[PDB]
Length: 291
Length: 290
Ligand SMILES: O=C[C@H](O)COP(=O)(O)O
Ligand SMILES: O=C[C@H](O)COP(=O)(O)O
Ligand code: NA
Ligand code: NA
Ligand SMILES: [Zn+2]
Ligand SMILES: [Zn+2]
Ligand SMILES: [Zn+2]
Ligand SMILES: [Zn+2]
Image 1 (cartoon, rainbow over the protein chains, first blue to last red):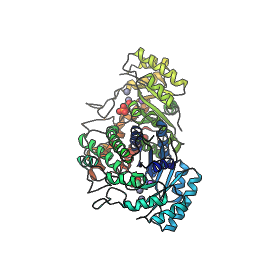
Image 2: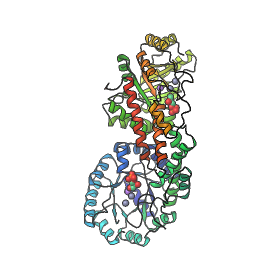
Image 3: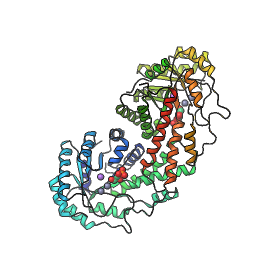
Image 4: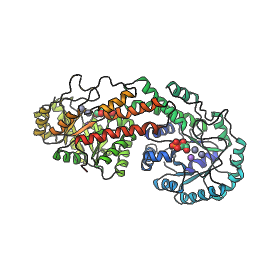
């Protein structure tokens, strides 16, 4: 059912596994994410960015998710606003039916980040909605400790080396796991990893075989993601991996049949590739069989 | 708002215009169709084939449509089951919240077509849902008896069309004398299947993106207008939407091999589909009918 984000992440926090947070922008992404969760018996964190919400309309974003939840009522589902940029954006997500909201104010000084986050928290918590915030651009663990105590935010995303998109590491992957463990120790709350796509080898091969160009993009290796969960990460933001796998198959259908224009012929194999990415990620993070 | 199919088509029947009936298989198609109707102030017929319903799930097909109607509550919208093949399929659509259903038994002999259609009608009408059936080329006298006894709300008579892009291996031709006779004898809304036109700008867009249309031909615009003058009120349109949508997808794929933001593919695809629908609404005379 559609539940508070913290309902899912407190269990993951206490038992020591990661729940993937998967972005979607339309029905095909959402269906494949849900079939993955049903097939791996895994909780689901479903994420929509502000841009995704503008593309779908927030009424359709929430509406499609609610339909999917009633289709799979046995799966714990949180619907999460990814990188909300204003109080008003977060307030609109709360009013529309989101069960989790992120307020990203990490580009501000500590005092202004805490101020705005706290404002979001008391609004969201009044409405039964959980809150994510971000600290770092890396994190100061003692800032994190104070930030969490005073804001009462439900989960925290500390900067430990990742970044959005595919072009993460200009060389070898590097995450500061000592800093992670200290944050986790001092805050004792669920933590979140942004920019956590791995770009597996098969997904990249699929994309390049379809004539795509990834441009030397490298994600977080699987072994770093597992070490992250061992360090205390409980929500693993994942988007790029899904897009590459999906568009790989769309490119492939276009290439191999120039007369094909049935949309289902493009998006059925795209859905399948995306679902498989999600299933494997669920097993990697340790959320499989957790229902 | 979401309304009986006959509510939209009775008005079109009385006032002599055609309402496009546009197929969809996902959010992108649906959104672009609704924005077209909103911008042309036009009633909408939204339809989903059995295959589309298996792809989306009937719960999602109705659910997305109901969300879209709430976003544009001033637009008369009917949600239509396209080419239902069984009574049970039509019954599931009625229960799921469709406001119109088509039962296609035209491959049966007259007596069996009428019997199955009548059974669907009794079921659908008990639930406040309108019914389309198919006959056929059509015998105008079969049509007259068929409609009187079945009490179907609208009829698709075969007059020369076919589904898909490949409609006429020779010159395009429709039997308009047959059409008018059917209209005269039945005096109900009529439906035209296989009514995609494949406009030249949509074909040019598809070929420029590397697409192959394999010498396909659609109904000329002039034939669509003549069919509405002859009494056609519901004009089934699918292929045109697919080609315009997939033309832009192919183009995005071609012009940036590093693009994998789905919105970068489907925003222009939506726009192109929207414009096809907008121009079709103006062609058929449903624009500015709200
Ligand atoms: O915040 C991270 C998400 O991947 C954002 O996706 P977006 O490209 O829709 O903003
Ligand atoms: O009934 C005619 C429809 O255009 C067919 O659509 P479909 O290809 O989803 O069956
Ligand atoms: Na987030
Ligand atoms: Na139909
Ligand atoms: Zn992020
Ligand atoms: Zn971030
Ligand atoms: Zn048809
Ligand atoms: Zn037909």
